[PDB]
């Protein structure tokens, strides 16, 4: 189920091989071995890393180049779902003390999600699944709100062949600042 | 496990026993045997049916009465997350052909969700988990968008001791009329 069935016998057609840790040797396509602590699946919805596309089709559509120097293109309006007038749907909301948040990316960032939200809801590309220890994604962090503060709160638009429709929180201070001023604390999962 | 530890040695204290298929014999508290196909946990969080409350405390807080005639109290503003001005966060959005949706409730209803969203994201009470085939919840329906239509789309507020923060779709005609007119089609899960 790694690749759509149509992509056989040669699913890696068009992909330049860099390092055999990664699918078709390309880190953008995520790891062969997936981090054993994100399950991603249930009986109703499964994680199709490329959607119904084959790997090279997926890179051509969602990156600037299928070649290794291509980079992923991200959605407009900070990835918020768009209303019928093409405006992102969100509002300023207060996060309460005790709430559990997680994040893919460095603490220089400003985007969090609720702890544990399934991957396919986040519309993140495959390379966010790369790991260093097999347990967890290499850029995955978990936090707890320690003092109430206001964020932009709203639904996640579909992208990268994923359905999206989780909720995301866009902070007005980066995570490092929020930790330093006592709004968030780090938790190790 | 099923009940918080402090609730022992008599966790069903205060619950009137009706039928031994249900926890403490109360259908409002959901099935002893949970439907073996349905996604409760999200990725890293497990499903606590009562949160940290004991059963009788849970019904006192979330229902009109602990007695068997008590009915669940639902959140204001259709259960949308509220902004800092106490207004629901949402906008009108066009659902696209091909989108997969599901719903807990009769087709006389107006609320739908992305197919497969984890139960803990929906802020629904435990009795929506009651199952007669043991496989799927009794009131559970799956649909696919066959023609575009506009819904109210937004995040789900925490309620019933659950974290919420899935996305919900509120239709302007009940689900039945969307099916009859070719906007949705029924699917067997
Ligand atoms: C998102 O969309 C909903 C629903 O709008 C309906 O569905 C859409 C898919 C689309 O087809 C729309 O064309 C369609 O209206 C919006 O909710 C509705 O908002 C209207 C007004 O904006 C409400 O109508 C009001 O109803 C009142 C009684 O319940 C009544 O007092 C009002 O009458 C007055 O106003 C009219 C002019 O608007 C005037 O002619 C009258 O004589 C009188 O002065 C008014 O009719 C609906 O009740 C709302 N429907 C629901 C289900 O709530 C929603 O505003 C929109 N949201 C965003 C953010 O765009
Ligand atoms: C949500 O807030 C942002 C940012 O405003 C800051 O945070 C809020 C919680 C509130 O306390 C504000 O007073 C703070 O300044 C709003 O974006 C701002 O919009 C104004 C309007 O032109 C603009 O001058 C600022 O530069 C914007 N700031 C940023 C960081 O973009 C946003 O409009 C608010 N959304 C609402 C109220 O729905
Ligand atoms: C890249 O490939 C080399 C094999 O020469 C391997 O040692 C290394 O671990 C790979 N990089 C990873 C897994 O990040
Ligand atoms: C990326 O590499 C390909 C060659 O493999 C080249 O065609 C393309 O122009 C490159 N883009 C750059 C260097 O920005
Ligand atoms: C309880 O309810 C189920 C279905 O609602 C029914 O099959 C059963 O006979 C009822 N009574 C008992 C004692 O189980
Ligand atoms: C439910 O019935 C009980 C009798 O067992 C009664 O005390 C109570 O008033 C009823 N519920 C409400 C909300 O009135």
Image (spheres, coloured by chain):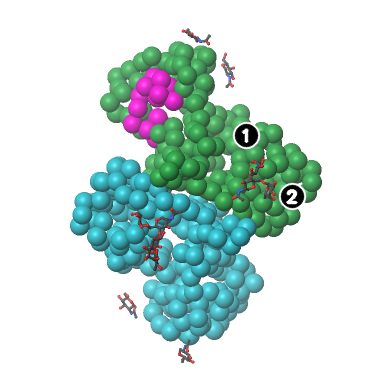
Chain colours: A green, B cyan
Q: Does the Cβ of the disc 1 residue fall within 8 Å of ligand 3?
A: no
Q: Is mark 1 on a helix, strand or loop?
A: loop
Q: Nearer the viewer, residue B150 or A1?
A: B150
Q: Nearer the viewer, residue A109 or A5?
A: A109
**Parent chain of label 2:** A
Task: Determine which residue is flagged by label 1.
Answer: A105
**Residue A107, x across and y down, in percent:** 69, 36
Q: Is B116 colored magenta in this rendering?
A: no
Q: Residue at left 41%, top 20%?
A: A60
Q: Nearer the viewer, residue A90 or A8?
A: A90
Quadrant in which the C terminus of chain A appears: top right
* Horizontal side, residue A15 vs residue A152: left or right: left
Q: Residue at left 44%, top 40%?
A: A86
Q: Is A55 colored magenta in this rendering?
A: yes
**Residue A31, x across and y down, in percent:** 50, 27
Residue extent of the magenta highlight: A48-62
Task: Determine which residue is flagged by label 2.
Answer: A183
Q: Residue B92 carries which label?
A: none
The quarter holding residue A54 reads: top left
Image quarter for ligand 1 equals: bottom left
**Residue B181, x across and y down, in percent:** 21, 54
Q: Residue at left 46%, top 64%?
A: B78
Q: Does the Cβ of the disc 2 residue fall within 8 Å of ligand 2?
A: no
**A20 up-or-down from B182: above or below:** above
Q: Which of marks 1 and 2 is in front?
A: 2
* Horizontal side, residue A6 vs residue A61: left or right: left
């Amino acid at each position: 189920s790694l690749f759509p069935a149509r992509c056989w016998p040669d699913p890696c057609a068009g992909i330049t091989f860099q390092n055999d840790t990664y699918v078709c040797g390309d880190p953008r396509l995520g790891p062969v071995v997936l981090p054993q602590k994100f399950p991603l699946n249930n009986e109703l919805r499964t994680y199709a890393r490329f959607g119904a596309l084959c790997p090279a089709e997926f890179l051509d559509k969602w990156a600037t180049d299928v070649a290794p120097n291509g980079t992923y293109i991200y959605p407009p309006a900070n990835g918020f779902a768009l209303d019928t007038e093409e405006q992102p749907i969100l509002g300023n909301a207060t996060l309460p003390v005790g709430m559990k948040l997680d994040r893919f990316g460095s603490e220089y960032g400003t985007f969090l999600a609720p702890l544990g939200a399934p991957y396919i809801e986040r519309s993140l590309p495959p390379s966010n699944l790369n790991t260093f220890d097999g347990m967890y994604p290499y850029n995955y962090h978990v936090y707890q709100v320690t003092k109430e503060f206001v964020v932009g709160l709203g639904p996640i638009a579909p992208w990268f062949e994923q359905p999206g429709m989780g909720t995301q929180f866009v902070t007005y201070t980066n995570v490092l600042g929020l930790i330093d001023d006592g709004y968030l604390r780090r938790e190790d999962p």
